[PDB]
Length: 558
Picture (spheres, rainbow, N blue to C red):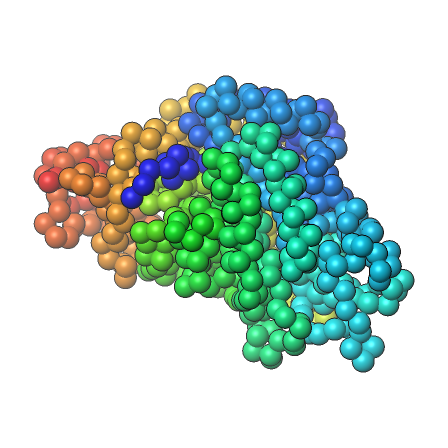
């Protein structure tokens, strides 16, 4: 085990668009982030990861980049960006930015030139192909709807886009492309950014000759897209030519990658990436074919995935741990219980799990307040292009009924985590003086930052306490992870141990009071923290009485 600031750091993810608006146009901006750095510092955050801040038409809210060297108009200036880095440095905070290089906006200069003629120098920066019998080159489907091939009538060829048609994929097989991307990365790294989070990092390498996908592959095509024969050669090349020249932390969003193949991206000996962002846990209850649909799950399934993810990282890799982010529903709604009676306690329980895993924890803006999913009714209330893609492919084709579709996307939509951060009880929760780009959840009157910061028993302050505890206990970062019983669907319990120091974490996922006898003659030395109190725990206790959703951390004897 080697110590790294990024293994011990508590990260906080900021979705600029919905964090804090400072000029009344309804859109979060960089000055808003700077304005809240003291709030985050009080919380105890060590580093901030911000979603795409580059010039973009926003077909995919920042993930379709028109100019990699320019700040998105709505977010501010290069000046604001440099100030953010500086104000953060002052507070001993490190900044991580989002690197979106699997594709670019179709308004990106390289693509504008690329589509102009078959002989343009930049034609090879993307993937162009002739029709096949007047049809698309092959049967590749797009994550965002319809075919992954878009016809261009000027040149009579189709271009590839795994995501939106406004997001053409870059030709990593072209050396000039890699070199230009490396140059772009150095531009941002030389400004002092401390980390890079790579968006869909495992799809850079395409399949030679683009052969059709089998009928079966069509039901799980992301898995086929991550089989590029040169993905690791490329990630490692990027490490040698760029990454290795700076003291930074790199996270890889390995979308589509099976857990067994994940280690090749993060084994420290391979010189590729540092922190793994896996989907196994966060989308454990998601259908792999109809990717918008959810199904029931049990704690035993949840904890069994955590154990597999932990063992796969093992000795040479490293994991990030999070239960929500901008591409998923809210943690308290998804993994806890967001009803009025259980929201705060279940929220605190997820907080406990999050800050005590053998991994870098990532907290998503607003989840430290227990923000919940938004009550979307009609299909036109969603903003997400992904949602619209699913709606077209599944509802407008008559494959699935609108009501059943909506029942599911209300539970799985990325938009659930994109409603404006709830700062206070004023109009629009204090997010903006204008009109929010996306509607604010009505529950902000009950759930807001100003209210919780001064309340010692608040969700915000529970996170603050847990972040302090993790900072104070090496075992909680580096301690080995052991699940006391992977088949238990009621009480989640595990130990974290480093040398002679051993700690226990427990969460009663049940709505009923539970008595839990510890195994292996384990006994309690002292309570580190617990959501309860009045639930007296004494030295040498080996039986815990847990109230519904109760949770806690204890130091064990020996």
